[PDB]
Image: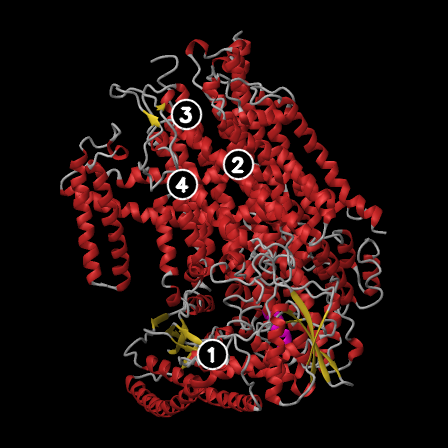
Amino acid sequence: EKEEAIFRSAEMALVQFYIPQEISRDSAYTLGQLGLVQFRDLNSKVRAFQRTFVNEIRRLDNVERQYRYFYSLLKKHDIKLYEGDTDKYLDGSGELYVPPSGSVIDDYVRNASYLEERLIQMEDATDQIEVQKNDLEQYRFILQSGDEFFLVNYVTGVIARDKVATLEQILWRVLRGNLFFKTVEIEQPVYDVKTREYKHKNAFIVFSHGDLIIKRIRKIAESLDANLYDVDSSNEGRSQQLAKVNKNLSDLYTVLKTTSTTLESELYAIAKELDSWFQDVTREKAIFEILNKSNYDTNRKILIAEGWIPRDELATLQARLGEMIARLGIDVPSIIQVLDTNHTPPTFHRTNKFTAGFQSICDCYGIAQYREINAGLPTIVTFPFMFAIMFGDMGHGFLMTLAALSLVLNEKKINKMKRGEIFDMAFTGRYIILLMGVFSMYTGFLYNDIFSKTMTIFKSGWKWPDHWKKGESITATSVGTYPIGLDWAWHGTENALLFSNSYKMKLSILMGFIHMTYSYFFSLANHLYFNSMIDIIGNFIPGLLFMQGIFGYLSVCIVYKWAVDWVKDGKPAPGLLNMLINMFLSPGTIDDELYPHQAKVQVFLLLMALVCIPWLLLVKPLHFKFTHKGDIMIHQVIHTIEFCLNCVSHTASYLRLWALSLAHAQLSSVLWTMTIQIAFGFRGFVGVFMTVALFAMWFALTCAVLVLMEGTSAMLHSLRLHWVESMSKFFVGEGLPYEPFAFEYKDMEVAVASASSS
Amino acid sequence: MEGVYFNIDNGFIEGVVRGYRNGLLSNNQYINLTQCDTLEDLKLQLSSTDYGNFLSSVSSESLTTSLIQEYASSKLYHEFNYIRDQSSGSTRKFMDYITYGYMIDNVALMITGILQRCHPLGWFDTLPTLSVATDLESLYETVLVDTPLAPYFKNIEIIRNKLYKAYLEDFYNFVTEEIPEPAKECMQTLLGFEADRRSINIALNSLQSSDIDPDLKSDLLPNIGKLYPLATFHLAQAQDFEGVRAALANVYEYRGFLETGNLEDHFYQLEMELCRDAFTQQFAISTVWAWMKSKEQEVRNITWIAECIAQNQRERINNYISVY
Amino acid sequence: VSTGKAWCCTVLSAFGVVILSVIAHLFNTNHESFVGSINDPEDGPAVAHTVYLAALVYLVFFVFCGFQV
Amino acid sequence: MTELCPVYAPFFGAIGCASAIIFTSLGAAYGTAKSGVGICATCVLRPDLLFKNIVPVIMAGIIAIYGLVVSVLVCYSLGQKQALYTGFIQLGAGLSVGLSGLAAGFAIGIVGDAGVRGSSQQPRLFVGMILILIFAEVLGLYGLIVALLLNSRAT
Amino acid sequence: KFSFSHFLYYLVLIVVIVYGLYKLFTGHGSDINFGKFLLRTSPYMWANLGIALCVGLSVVGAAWGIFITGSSMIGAGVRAPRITTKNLISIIFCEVVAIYGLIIAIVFSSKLTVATAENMYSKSNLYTGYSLFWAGITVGASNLICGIAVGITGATAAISDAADSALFVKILVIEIFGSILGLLGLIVGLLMAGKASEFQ
């Protein structure tokens, strides 16, 4: 069966395609709709303008230009494309047995070339008549003015509403203390050719007495884009001009209705099929762009193509090409010549709907080195569960689980449905969010938090004194230990913060160390897989010794300090952070003895960690210097110094688990106190109203501020822990994306691309 | 320090500007455009560069050198107007002052009255009024008083060069006062070069006019940069090309670079040197000026190559100016 | 009336019914986390009754908005 | 009064309560103003990106929420005859959270402006924007944490 | 030449000089008794100011470097969004600066304890007050300096990586030096407060 590629990327094989030149187009369609081949660019060192199939692309690109121009025209006149599923039914998108388009592409090219000119002609006609339409409408609006005349002679026209101010100022400097001006705002905007959109406009009139300065006013108004109009000096002449204008509008509308109807009919005929034309032309252009990457041997008359395909899919490729050759009946060799190569193969991870989101989030940092360990498979669990440690509330985890289930249960309904961007982001992460919610419920159970409040499902390990006076500062006694989760006896105590901080800080340190160690062992597994024992001995072993002997020492020390009953032993509880500091700043002088011979072990670990530094610097480069028959000294020294410093900085940065956990807990408690708990203090129908409204506020802020506003905080910080703390231990990265040659529904919204993306 | 406060407003701007600087055509890409054999081939090859699909709406039959130049200039102007739109305060004023030069160019080109605005960055609300402003007497008190050129004003070449003198002096003062130290030095040097170019060109124009008095050029020579005041005064007193050579003999830079070769090529070469040097400062707004000049030269080179493949005459195809 | 507001208020009122019902039950049973403090209301069942009435108000809203779903 | 509980002791507590909300609110205001200028500049062309670009102002708001939390917590620790120890505990909590949230809000404003602009020019910059912006938010978060640690010792 | 801030600087300088001369000439120079100010002042002001300024200046430096380098890398990321994940180590080392301040604030908060009135202003309590004050200032100011430096360096690294990915590597060494500076500041703060006892 096909090997799963989630632990490591799928095994690639380089295939050389000996394609006879006559069947090249059919073959390219076959293995493009098959969808498992990523072609190597053999003509990489040949300039694109002189490449083998440049003209076949150029003609189809002109056709695509014409189709996107048609789409622009349909949007201009508000027509909706058919977008039928005929292309989806024909292109199996997972089935390779489909015949390619025949000579129909040449018909597409001819039709497109003719039809573009047709549309240009009718658009020019409709545009010209629309220009005179707008002009005569403005003329009428000028003439409809019953009386806007004062004072020898005048000139009048229409300006855009913004330009009227600057034109008035310019004329006021043409005529200083002598300008007479009025304007009337047109009720609605009108179409302008230059902007290809409606603009607000204003009629204007100015009065003057000198032919030279009247010419100046007209010439300064035509600049700044005023449309000037001659108006009779009397109401009778203005009425005559208005009647003439109305008759001209009647004729203009008579021709405009027919022109617009015919043009819109052509656009409607376009809409029913333009989408399929664009799909076919896009596929054909992609086909030629793939064929360019083939070496065109003219003597042998064959395209020597190359491509990456998974080995488990090699048989599928052979079968499907055997099917297409049977279709064509050429009986050609159609050589699928798999060959060895030194080229870095692409990193293909075969992901289900469940692991797809985790793979996308892990490889958004970087694509893994070929057949190295995939970080996404550990991420599936670690990312949601670090999110949960930081989030850690059962009420909010339950809300998040319900939100995710609303996407997972209805999964088939939101799929095959338009999703926008934010809702699409929510849907693609639906299983990520589901695991976040579930692990957050578990974490809040361990934190014993449902919203602000604690669960009381087991007998507390702390028992209060037998009796006390009201207001007495009592202290509990340890009758036992709480089975699972934090003891509910800590709720509402004034020293709850001390124990909670100790717990969550040590939890952060311990679990961060464990996660770092687990991720770092992927370095060992990678070196074993790549047979790089030199990386094991020079990098893995000393780095592991350093990391353990300091921070894993701290980890086992934390668990040991929990494992010792200091009050029963009568020994002073050590200052654990102070002891860690003294391990470096004053070795040997152990303050409070945690365990026998702690000084010797402490100084031994210090010396071992120190020794691991020369080990890391030297062993890997010196092997290269001696045995290769060092140049990697600089890379090794910078890598090891950053490793040593990143160990400390990563142990520090894992404190954000405790940080976000405590902040979320405190925000939830404060929000509960501020919003809903006030309502419990009042009674009567005023109390009922306060309870209803304050619960509305509490839930709105819980969903907004806590679940959504601060859940994104926790998930982004878990992304931080993974890209930075987890993957940098082992993730080599800088791989090559798989992204094979495959057909897709390239929706015509790509008309935004290649026209607004440069 | 330089970058401590710089990134509060200009960090995004400066990062995007050097992003464009990385998109400038390299010598290899100019060579690839040179080897092209048709305007459609140049369109495709240039689409392979950071220009992308900008002529994507243009067919090979509509494609002409004028359209290529217009689209390249439009892309540059859209990028500049994006950076200016995202700018605020001091950098916004710096970019407005950059636009004032094109405003003066548009003023001089349009008063020639046909001559349109011909430059999008020099546009202002009353610019087309200059096409119809035949009376130079009405120029300031009617049209330009509303424009940002009002502080500068006080045949057309006299007006153009007076406006450039006032503009360059005011912009040098603005650079000195309102621009941090590295960008201050870089912009002061760039303005020294610009004023030197203006002074040399104006002197060589006065070479062709008998009415060009030495004191008349005092209203015209900016007296800014390395040539100032000494070489500027010598150019003012200079009567002919020999006087220009004697004046430029007194400076280190631009010495021996007007006595031989093409003068425009040498000015553009030195400008590219200065822009390349200005790009080295990491938290300086002078990177914007360097980018603008580099892109203008790039558009010139592209148009040059487009001509050399549209009208052949390919012997001239390699005389473009580039440091990248 | 609109489907968006109907769904929003239906979900909010469902959470209202559930959460205020459990809060009223915990007050009515004198649970320490709600009554154990001196700063809490002194008589559990009394505030439990008003929280229960608020839960019924959200029940009315839930059922109504269901009638407009 | 007493040597441990001077009459001027509540001054530090009250001024820390004020300081928390004040400085976190100025940080949030700078963040909201800068990022909102970015959003309004960006969404003139592409209003479809409103609910992406809204993140930086939201994070600025949560900074002020942290300030509100600290101010409330220290406010309910105030008393007329409170010790000078708890007075300076409240002062330290308020000052820490205020200054930290102020710096975080400034960083959030600048980064959010740059990010909304870039992620409008380059959509792949959204994850980068938000991941830098969370790293700015976490600094105000750290200040909140220190304020909580200090306030845990108020009496 | 005038500015309001410098006017107040010179005004307060003149006022302090005049007050000092007045006290000194009248034989009351010992009234200005900064030492007795240090003795009488509550040790908790020093301790909590140390903690608050430690974390506050660490966060200021972290945020300052963060927006410097983040704005630079978002701007450079417009053409090359690949720059984000590659140069994010700059944001990381800026944040680590604030984490240092948080750690030091935790350590110093361990020292905060209610000292008895009979033992309020002892040698040990004054010593620990001054120790926490100046150690918090040391860590916070060193962290501010290092955060600004790392942000500047990471901004330059992001822009250079946008120019060419090969130029990134050697600037990361500069970022490492900037982080070592803050680490040294943290360890020196620990040493300064290492022998400071709790308030007792």
Tell me whether the residue at label 2 lies in contact with that at label 4, contact meaning CB atoms closer than 8 angstroms. no
Residue that sits furthest to the top in the current view: E27
| Tag 2: amino acid | Ile
- In the rendered image, residues at marks 4 and 1 fall on the same chain: yes
Q: Is D131 left, or right, of A544 in this rendering?
A: left
- Label 4 sits on a secondary structure element that is helix
Nearer mark to the viewer, of 3 and 2: 2
- A103, A406: nearer the viewer: A406
Q: Earlier in the sequence, mark 2 or mark 1?
A: 1
Residue under label 1, please give it.
Answer: A88
Residue under label 2, please give it.
Answer: A509
| Tag 1: amino acid | Lys
- A261, C47: nearer the viewer: C47
Residue under label 4, please give it.
Answer: A664
Magenta stretch, overall SS: helix
| Tag 4: amino acid | His
- Label 2 sits on a secondary structure element that is helix
Label 1: chain letter:
A
- Label 3 sits on a secondary structure element that is loop
> Label 3 to label 2, Cα distance in Å?
23 Å
- In the rendered image, residues at marks 2 and 4 fall on the same chain: yes
> Label 1 to label 3, Cα distance in Å?
67 Å
> Label 4 to label 1, Cα distance in Å?
48 Å
- In the rendered image, residues at marks 3 and 2 fall on the same chain: no
Where residue B53 appears, x then y in whole percent?
60, 73
Q: Which residues are magenta?
A: B67-74
Q: To which quarter of the image does residue A256 belong?
A: bottom left
Which numbered tag is attached to residue D153? 3
